[PDB]
Every structure is written in structure tokens, then in C-alpha cells.
Amino acid sequence: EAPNQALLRILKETEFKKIKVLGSGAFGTVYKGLWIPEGEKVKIPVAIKELREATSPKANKEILDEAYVMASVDNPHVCRLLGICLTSTVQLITQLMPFGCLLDYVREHKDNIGSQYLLNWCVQIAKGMNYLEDRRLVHRDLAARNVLVKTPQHVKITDFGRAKLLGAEEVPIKWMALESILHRIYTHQSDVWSYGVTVWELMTFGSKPYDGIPASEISSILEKGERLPQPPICTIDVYMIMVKCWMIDADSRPKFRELIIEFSKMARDPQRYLVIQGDERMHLPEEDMDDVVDADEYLIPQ
Ligand SMILES: CN1CCN(c2ccc(Nc3ncc4nc(Nc5ccccc5)n(C5CCCC5)c4n3)cc2)CC1
Ligand SMILES: [Cl-]
Image 1 (cartoon, helix red, strand yellow):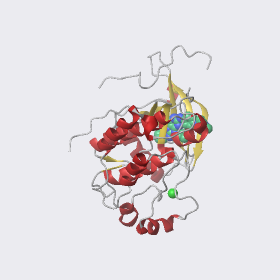
Image 2 (cartoon, rainbow, N blue to C red):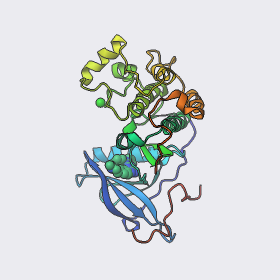
Image 3 (cartoon, rainbow, N blue to C red):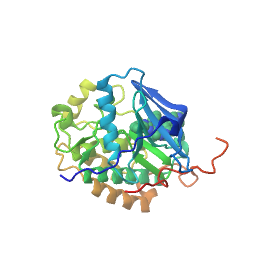
Image 4 (cartoon, rainbow, N blue to C red):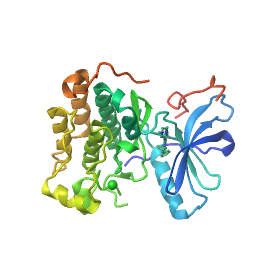
């Protein structure tokens, strides 16, 4: 086990301003923001994640764990933490994704969403997931909701709160593998299953898995050998890949690097693998912004 030498960056509240609430839920809320690095003359669009006035340590322990992980990852399809604020309750500052989470995005723009885009997102998500495997990280919460859109072409994974190192002792049932549901066993292969469902959400355009079904039931349903239905737009090949992710034997399940390859192939001839109406037709997209720089463009030594 190599040492983790990731730098953790501490940011003064003066450095950035919250502009809007992108989302609020539970303990904490997320704000669109602008961050200006000290003496740098760059403005970086950011999302700031903060919990409540309530500052309970247990909450803080959880947030910081999440920050730790985000600080430690560097991939194009993985979200990275820029810095943290220690003002009163802690805040996580990370690059902003203008178009939001993917799950919302498919639902909003389904009429204008191409097959090519869908296959690419699969490729990119598998790329992100493979990188986590490389770092021996298990996301343990893969879902469409946890995927964010920098641009229609570019997407990255997020929400590393449940993330853990492989083989470490240390709840979305529908996403969870069966082995995990019965025994709380998590592995990269468990992650792959969750990926399968994530793929299904996109194909199904944001439809909720196992809709109308109580979670307690789900374990039995999976036990029976029941699985999610093949989506209308899905070719047999694409669905078949999905089903492989839902195999009882985790080893039987496809590796993330294999998933990248297979979906890659399909993206070369997207129309053959997904059938969508008017696929060809579809196309997809404060005063001073001169200094604006994207987080990807903004780099620091090390
Ligand atoms: C219909 N509306 C469309 C616009 N919209 C939206 C939401 C988020 C973004 N961007 C963005 N960026 C970074 C984020 N980081 C977290 N979360 C997060 C997790 C860990 C560390 C830092 C942030 N989020 C969450 C995703 C949904 C609510 C905000 C983030 N969201 C852009 C537009 C809300 C829905
Ligand atoms: Cl759930």
C-alpha cells in the first residue's frame, strides 16, 4: 500500500462567494459559486457543499471522509475536490458542472438525446469507474443521480461519501448488488452491478428502478432471478451487457475495462446498437467572465 501524497488545499471564505443554491437536501445544501485563488487573477466556477448550522461532530467526520477521497483522485471522468473551507462548519469546494446530474439531464432532454451520447456516457462512466478500481476504491453508491454533466459530451462521477478502500471493514437497495444486500459485501464487481443499473436508467430515460416496489422485497425479487426489463431503445446486445452486470456470481460479471471496450465498439456504430426515433435530428447545446477558467484548465503544482 503506497502512501497517499495528495495535497489538501485550505481555502479562506474571502476567496469565494456563494451565488445560488443548486440543491438542498438533508443535512447540507450545495451552492453555485465563484472562487478566486489568492493573487491568481482567475475566477473558477465551483460548487460548495455545506451542511447545516448544526455542527455535530459525527456529521463532520462523514464530510471530511468524503473530502479525503475527492482530494485523492485525478481522472477526467472523476470529480475532484479543489479545496475545503473551515469556517464554522466545513465546506467542500469542487469544480462546478453546469448541466447538473445526469439523471436529471436525461429526463429533461430525452426528446433531444441521441444514441451516440448515451453510449458515450456509458464509456465515460466505465472509464471513471475503472480508474477508481485502479486506486482500489469502491464507490458503493454508483447511480445516474451521482453522475454530473460538465457538458453533454463530458461527464464525471461524484458522491464519494460512501466510498471505501477494497477489503476494508469500515442505503440504496435498488442499485446494490445482491451479495451486498444480503451480506454487506462490496467489491469492484459489486460496483459493476450498480453500473448496470445506472446504464439502465439512461436507456430507460431516468425511469426509477423497480418502481412501485418496496426495498425489503427487492432482495427476494433478485433472489428469484428477476431482473430489470429490457428498455425499448435497447438492442439485444446492449441489454445483454446489462444482464451480465446482474449475474449472481460477481466474478462472472464484466470488468470495468471490458465494459469500456465493448461500449466503445458500439459508439462507432451507435445506430446499430440503440434504436431511437429521429436520432439523426438530435443535437445538444456575472457581467465579467473574461477571467473565467474551468477547473480542468486550472492546475497547481504537484
Ligand atoms: C434542474 N436543475 C438544473 C440545474 N441544477 C444543477 C445542479 C447541479 C449543478 N452542478 C453541480 N456541480 C457540482 C455539484 N456537486 C454536487 N454535489 C457535490 C457532492 C460532493 C461534493 C461537492 C458537491 N452537486 C449536486 C448535484 C445536484 C445538486 C448539486 C453538484 N451540482 C448544476 C446544475 C439543479 C437542477
Ligand atoms: Cl433505493
